[PDB]
Image (tube, rainbow, N blue to C red):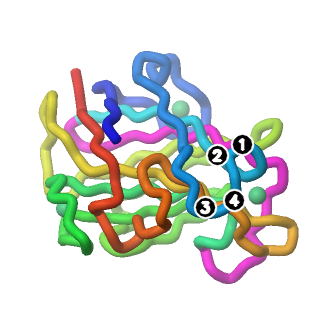
Amino acid sequence: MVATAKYGTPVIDGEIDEIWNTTEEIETKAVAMGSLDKNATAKVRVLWDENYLYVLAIVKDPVLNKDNSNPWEQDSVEIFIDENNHKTGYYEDDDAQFRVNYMNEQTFGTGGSPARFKTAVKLIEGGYIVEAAIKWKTIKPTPNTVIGFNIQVNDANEKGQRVGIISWSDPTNNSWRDPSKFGNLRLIK
Ligand SMILES: [Ca+2]
Ligand SMILES: [Ca+2]
Ligand SMILES: [Ca+2]
């Protein structure tokens, strides 16, 4: 799976900057749990600059819940990055997993850090908008650079149970530990 992200610097606030319309929109259709017509999915736009990767995720989710103690079993979005795009079967120092729920509470998997994660969440009719900035850790990207990338949407019901797991490139729910499951994202001018 291959996608592209246009160069640009949006303001992290949950509002949709005009610039987001200049880059392609991808959809999370790789089902691991649940179904597209019944569970949380997202329309995603991606931008980038020399210092950060920017992600705009518009999530469709009629019931918001975060009662479960496990952050991944709360309504939330997970963003995966493989900076050198080695597509390894385990996480290298440059690989990372970031997570943020609908209440804008951040949590981190391997490689993730609050020092490199800025987020804003705005609720909307039928769901919520996540806008994030991920600071590069090992690279200073230039046009046509390609990284490993994926975005996952966790869907929890009113009972605090996760009923949906859907991402862009991974239908096996192994992104948290396997970079070879991410897709390819080309950073273009
Ligand atoms: Ca914004
Ligand atoms: Ca890597
Ligand atoms: Ca939900």
For residue 178, side relative to residue 92 (left or right) = right
Q: Amino acid at mark 4?
A: Gly
Q: Label 3, label 4: how many angstroms apart (C-alpha)?
A: 6 Å
Nearer to us of marks 4 and 2 is 4
Query: CB atoms at circles 2 and 1 under 8 Å apart?
Result: yes
Q: Earlier in the sequence, mark 2 or mark 3?
A: 2
Q: Which residue is mark 1?
A: 60
Residue 76 in the image: state x and y as whole percent.
62, 59
Q: Residue furthest bottom?
A: 69
Q: Which residue is mark 4?
A: 34
Q: Are the residues tagged 4 and 1 within 8 Å (C-beta)?
A: no
Q: Quadrant of the C terminus?
A: top left
Q: Residue at x 32, y 30 (%)?
A: 4
- Label 3 amino acid? Ile
Kindly indicate the quadrant of the structure image that contains residue 178. bottom left
Label 3 residue SS: strand
Q: Is residue 174 above or below residue 14?
A: below
